[PDB]
Image (cartoon, rainbow over all chains, first blue to last red; front, side, top):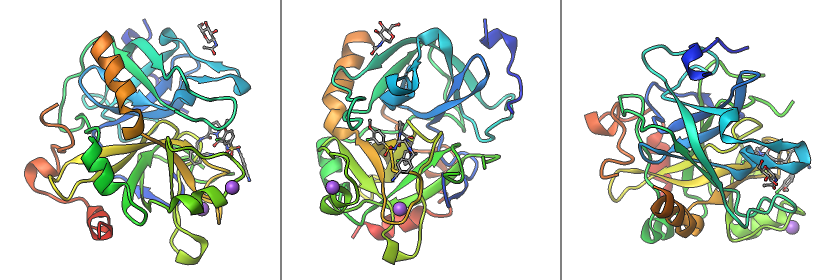
Length: 11
Length: 251
Length: 28
Ligand SMILES: COc1ccc(S(=O)(=O)N[C@@H](CC(=O)NCc2ccc(C#N)cc2)C(=O)N2CCC[C@H]2C(=O)NCc2cc(Cl)ccc2CN)cc1Cl
Ligand SMILES: *[C@@H]1O[C@H](CO)[C@@H](O)[C@H](O)[C@H]1NC(C)=O
Ligand code: NA
Ligand code: NA
């Protein structure tokens, strides 16, 4: 399972 | 990567991870060829038999990574895609002929100790180095065995195989746009790419100018690391005219 | 680019990685 990435990259 | 080892820090600073946005997961490997362009396998983006057909907004690229799963704060950089280009004659129906794609980033990535582009071969370097017995290096975060997954980037060095041996190892029609690599059953040593390593680079270090060149792209294999089978790689030089056409036209 | 294929932590510092010699030795 992957560590969550900063939300700015999913926007 | 099967039967490889942990990469050293900064050993492959051109390595790129293709990352799916939702659900968040590894999709493929890829490589950095300039501050705006990333090279990968076409089948990482388009493979109808598996209902795979990604669009730009489906994906991210993560550059400068070492750990497979961690968010490497202050080290990795994450980029969005402006546009995907797949080779117009990519043959996903039969044999993955011309298994190559380019991705243009929305914004240039800053180079660092951990982020740096690999060279693409010219005709002469390809002719000099793409010879049976000569070894290249394959890197990726793919599976450790055909049938688990690594904590960090894996590396393996593998010899290019004579074309007739590649051909005789498989029922698949091999083309001039592929080459194969791996040890023979009798050679003892082993290793191969595997699922998840797709799209990553097969690189060689030129003894003429001490620079790393990407000669291949991880493309396909019958299983992973099977005796008598070999890994098949997209022949980057053979498709370089297409690469240059795309970059010159769109960048 | 002009600087392609030269790694900051290796070639740029004249440091060798642990297995690149294996590649060089294969280039007969
Ligand atoms: C359309 O073209 C193809 C369609 C399929 C296959 S394949 O079945 O041989 N391999 C396929 C899928 C596979 O491995 N099936 C499991 C499997 C297990 C045992 C045998 C035997 N005998 C055959 C297959 C593959 O590599 N594909 C299908 C699409 C993507 C690519 C891939 O996984 N590439 C990664 C890879 C790259 C390399 Cl260099 C070495 C191994 C691997 C992992 N197999 C080759 C071509 Cl060229
Ligand atoms: C894949 O996706 C594109 C765009 O969404 C679509 O137009 C195309 O028909 C699909 N199949 C391909 C490219 O083989
Ligand atoms: Na054959
Ligand atoms: Na094998």
